[PDB]
Image (cartoon, rainbow, N blue to C red):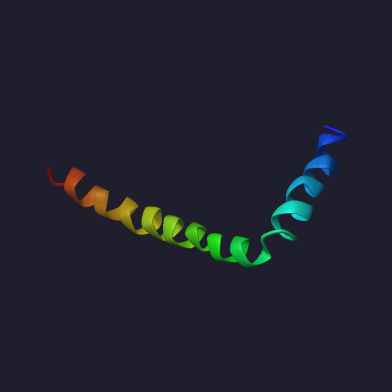
Length: 52
């Protein structure tokens, strides 16, 4: 790596934050529900496997 490091930095930062600063902020919300889903369900799936 040597050029793909700065080329990528400007590929998303100067494209996904200047053209969709209002949408990207709202879309990022999906990261919260996804983690919370996998974070709370990873425990429930164990209740049935540890009993049946």
